[PDB]
Image (cartoon, rainbow over the protein chains, first blue to last red):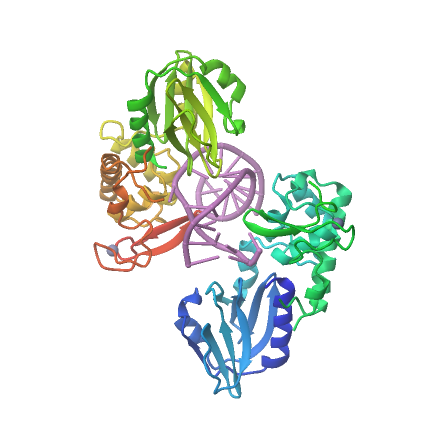
Length: 263
Length: 267
DNA sequence: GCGAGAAACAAAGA
DNA sequence: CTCTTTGTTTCTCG
Ligand SMILES: [Zn+2]
Ligand SMILES: [Zn+2]
């Protein structure tokens, strides 16, 4: 999941679990709680979920007043709400039990993480990750973006995916955005023109905000209907009729139009 | 690679290339020759490799009389000897060709460097970097070492890594030394006792010489090492300390992965 | 001071 | 990027 998907998860959870008291926390894979499962159990049991925030692809549960739970799903993490008598599934790892149901975290890869952070350490935690700005016209400043790009010979796709220029792009939306901006994924950042950078800036926001609006991509989101390159190897570019190509860039599957996006 | 690995490489090359005349030097990544690839090609082509020395982690090729080739392998740099018709490999950057084969330099991450330096600028090259002493009893004076430590607030692990106190420790051997001397990586230099310092000094020499003897550490020319079997903490996270039984922990210290026994090494 | 970060880069690991 | 980490050194930041 990318930013839009995480934000969709944040909204669904906000509607459903805010106000709920945690009766118990149990784990079949405590190691995914990097800060220590027993500590987390001690501090959050009996507390009320007050809210759920997001920064980048990170979810932030406001539980009690002193601590926050920072959850990253990584590649395959998924939350579901189940009844109390719900049977286990193979890749369930963690559960928060409430008086009339439970919030289960599952992850086939076991990459996702929980981190218990004191409230005062949340801003620092994100500063320290060097996470870039939210992809909004409010936060994502084109001048700073331009300045950083002009200073780098990094290929634009991998650089965008670092999360430092702007937060929230994954493999799917980076390909979408480069297509929309007519930029080759292996173009060196400092070869981008000013106008090209402007369009890239806006396409980042426009695609990610649109995808939030459609509840993310499901491959129950609807953004998958609006994908122009991801998964369309061989099909015709809607803009020029060229066959969409798939190459590997810094180890990642990459879809692009060979006419609309040229190095 | 660290000092022991560079020494192992220096030995293997010394045995195999001294006396060879350079027929050609070619590069697919000329930018790693920081002083200018073309000048290097022009100055070394046709000359005989007379010897290879080492200072710290640096290799020093004596080729001809007027110039020295100073090579640093940084993180992953690797030399090998191949036949003349050898296929290229993905991360090969430079080759030095001889009449019966070639010496190829490869480096996945492209951190490694070559520099052409005139012979009478070699000693100043090293002085200018402030490289510390070689880790031998003869060169590594405990008295200077002590004075430098007593005067500094630096955390001991990053200070050792700087190469100025003593030359040749990298992330592996610094972790190993500190565990042997029972010193916490984050301990400030000036809080070290004279007896700690003495033990530290000796452990540096003892580990780096045992490492050279064992042909270096082969984790993932030079690649037949045995020292990796003698490691006590580096990469042993979650395993038992061999001295006290406690769980080896890993933390980050000045940006580097750091393995210690928290029982044996208290800050 | 100092330590922290970042640059240079690619691929493996969790 | 899903993100972090890696056998180094040199450099700028705060
Ligand atoms: Zn097209
Ligand atoms: Zn111990």
